[PDB]
Image (spheres, coloured by chain):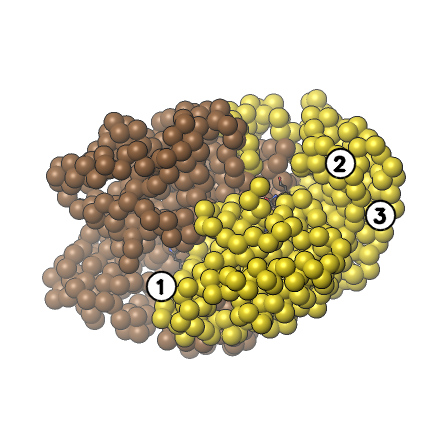
Chain colours: A yellow, B brown
Amino acid sequence: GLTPEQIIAVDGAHLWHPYSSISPVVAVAAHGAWLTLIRDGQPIEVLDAMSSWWTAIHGHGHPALDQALTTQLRVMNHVMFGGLTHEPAARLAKLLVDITPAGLDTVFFSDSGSVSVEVAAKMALQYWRGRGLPGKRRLMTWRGGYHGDTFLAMSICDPHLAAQVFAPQVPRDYDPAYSAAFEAQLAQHAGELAAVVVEPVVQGAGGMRFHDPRYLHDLRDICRRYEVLLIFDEIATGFGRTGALFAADHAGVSPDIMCVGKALTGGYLSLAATLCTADVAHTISAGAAGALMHGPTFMANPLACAVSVASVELLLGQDWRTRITELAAGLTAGLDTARALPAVTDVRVCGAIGVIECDRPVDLAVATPAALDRGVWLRPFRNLVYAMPPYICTPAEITQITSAMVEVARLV
Amino acid sequence: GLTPEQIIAVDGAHLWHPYSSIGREAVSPVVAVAAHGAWLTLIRDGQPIEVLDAMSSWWTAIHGHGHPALDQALTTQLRVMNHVMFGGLTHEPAARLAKLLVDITPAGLDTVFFSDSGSVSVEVAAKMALQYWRGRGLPGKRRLMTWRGGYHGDTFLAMSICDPHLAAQVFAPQVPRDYDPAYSAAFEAQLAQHAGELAAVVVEPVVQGAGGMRFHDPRYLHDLRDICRRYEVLLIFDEIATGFGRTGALFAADHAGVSPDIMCVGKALTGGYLSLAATLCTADVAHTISAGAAGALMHGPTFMANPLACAVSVASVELLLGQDWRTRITELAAGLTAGLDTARALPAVTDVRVCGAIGVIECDRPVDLAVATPAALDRGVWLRPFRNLVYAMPPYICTPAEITQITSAMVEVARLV
Ligand SMILES: Cc1ncc(COP(=O)(O)O)c(CNc2ccc(CCCO)[nH]c2=O)c1O
Ligand SMILES: Cc1ncc(COP(=O)(O)O)c(CNc2ccc(CCCO)[nH]c2=O)c1O
């Protein structure tokens, strides 16, 4: 065992944190929408406004998910997915194929979002090889995107590695001229392109930007006409977050390949999935390799699959759309006051996502204590103060979150 | 819920398996309904049967499945904190595991980067090496060098250093089993001409797993360490398969008594409960990266340092260290040697080799799966031959009788070949 002080000592000496060098606050518990943190030697309750980075949609320690995990743990923790299959994987695959955009009928489980993106790339590349067009090996996307930290995933992240094709930043408002320009650029690269890869509707890590769903309809059309596969990365947007079950649903379009993760497991365990159409699967399967050449050690882990099944079932068994609509209303109302702030450039809400865009990078040394002082855990990045609250947050808790966000913006 | 029939129907229509097809599988997956200790419960011809997990579910299940201590560690952490973001927050599980790993790994490795899988941990190791040299003002050192027969995962960068059989990396010849100073001299010569271009050498120490279950004299690792130091190239050991006692030492590097600059671990890390991997580096590497223009290691997965995965790993590592694991492995190695001995005389058998809790029969031809599967299943053993290899890496908890059962099944496969 270790005291909060010993943890800090070990952490400072031995632990790499995300995108950091070699001060973290000690977290000692999580329950519902609340974290227990240690501040100045004292335990404090704070709202998990970030849902622990998009994951904890049902909050922490939900009895349904806890029990799903303990139930599976009693019977089978893990077995290899080579030559074996199991109920959690089958139940989850069945669910995912049923709730995702039409045509997505096969499921490849992996351990993280970055890996699922590379699997999606593998699918697209092997697809065209299966069609006898191995020259189609590049990827195209628009600027402002983020798809993970592995080397292939890095290649399609906003440039500001494989050399990929980048269209200009997709605007918030629909402009037919943007779609026309996108098509013209894609046209001259078509013989080079395996796929277009984008985050539908919401671009997260690249700057929490929202774009009109109509752009997705245009992409589907362009890709269809120029024979380029369309890949949607819904790792952040999936499972109700943007007001629809999957962001693609706002445009009513189905991609050829789709990545999901994060909220998939309710934030309990690492799991991701890459789905593709029957056409893609068969073409790869009929190809020279005769198979999709990927398969991680812990593929389709029974424990992760079991808790994911329960998380998805919990989500579908309630009126999630109304819940999200209520959250969106709460965020909008709560953030409105920020608009008039001198350092605030924009305020925007999309489903259970709320963003205050500031005129300068937000200083964590100031924002963090300001948020903690108000009983809220916020993690600003670049010039953004934002939140993606758990779906179980009450109106009062959303108000607490938004008022903390506003006071952070005010300090900037 | 689903019946085994419904599971197979769903599986066939909607599930990708590792390196497999949809609709074109010669052999359908077998339904697994339970796992406890060294045994899996599988559905054969509709009958539930118990079979030995001879592969430890790919090196992972070192304490067997559903070990009471590990189950408890998981449920204990589940009651308090399932997960929190590792950005700006830290927690006891991560700290306890980091402290443990820093203490039991080869000397010098005192920083720990957690990731969600082996392939990712390898990519992190690569990033560390590349950023290290950028921090030294030598961005030209960006390629990797390895020897053939290796395997390091299936993300695109990981693939580039896997045995060809992508970034174009530098490949030295297959390292031989027995120590030949000539091999090391030639390795040095090849590396020497690429030095200004090389960020790191990356290899599996002592045992190459997925690349063909080959063993090599640990002295080669001593040579690599020396070569790397003299030519200013970092050394990366991928111990994702060899770690935590598997080869008869706590880490395979310990056989050679050398310390890499960077090291990857995974698999047995969590006792095979959940996916978790870690990349460790020296203080020098960490400091050089932190002092560079970038000012930080530019990597950070959403689910980094998951409390549940860390908690079960702490229990698994503590369980291993709290017992005489070295003697357990020695006993396993002896049981494997005794059990596989009779295969040495089989017509189609080219080699029989054992290293710690690893047993391999190498044939002179490819192993037909349609012959091997029912043969092993009939004998209550789950085996996964590939190419010309029939092999096992059983859980450390296997009794002498279970080892006899496993080896007897392997020999029969070798006989049928
Ligand atoms: C769309 C999409 N595709 C792929 C991934 C990667 O999957 P992973 O391999 O499991 O990490 C992510 C998740 N990565 C991030 C999400 C959110 C932030 C916000 C805070 C930045 O400081 N930063 C991230 O890096 C994703 O959102
Ligand atoms: C040394 C080493 N370094 C890195 C990795 C990659 O880490 P991952 O990303 O967690 O896979 C591995 C992976 N080992 C295997 C991977 C896949 C199967 C097939 C399983 C079929 O059910 N069997 C494996 O042994 C590895 O051995």
Q: Position of residue A6 (x, y in %)?
A: 57, 24
| Chain ID, mark 1 | B
Where is residue B270 shown, x and y percent of the image?
A: 47, 45
Q: Nearer the viewer, residue A307 or A178?
A: A178
Quick check: A256 left or right of B233?
right
Residue to which mark 3 is pinned: A332
For disc 1, the marked residue is B382
Q: Amino acid at mark 3?
A: Thr
Of discs 3 and 2, which sits in the foreground?
2
* Left or right of residue A272, residue B210 in this image: left
Q: Is residue B283 left or right of residue A335?
A: left
Which disc, if any, is residue A358? 2
Callout 2 environment at 10 Å: few (<14), some (14 to 19), or many (20+)? many
Q: Disc 3 on helix, strand or loop? A: helix
Marks 2 & 1, CB-CB < 8 Å contact = no
Quarter of the image for residue A87 reads bottom right
Residue drawn at x 46%, y 29% is B289
Tell me which chain the residue with mark 2 is part of.
A
Q: Is B402 placed left or right of A374 in the picture?
A: left
Marks 3 and 2, Cα distance to the nearest angstrom?
A: 17 Å
At label 3, counting other C-alpha atoms closer than 10 Å, the crowd grade (few under 14, some 14-19, many 20 or more) is many
Residues under labels 2 and 1: Cα distance?
59 Å
Vertical arrangement, residue A47 with respect to residue A234, above or below: above
Taking depth in this image into account, of A332 and A215 the one nearest to the observer is: A215
Residue drawn at x 42%, y 59% as measured from the top left: A294
Question: At numbered mark 1, what does the secondary structure look like: helix, strand or loop?
Answer: strand
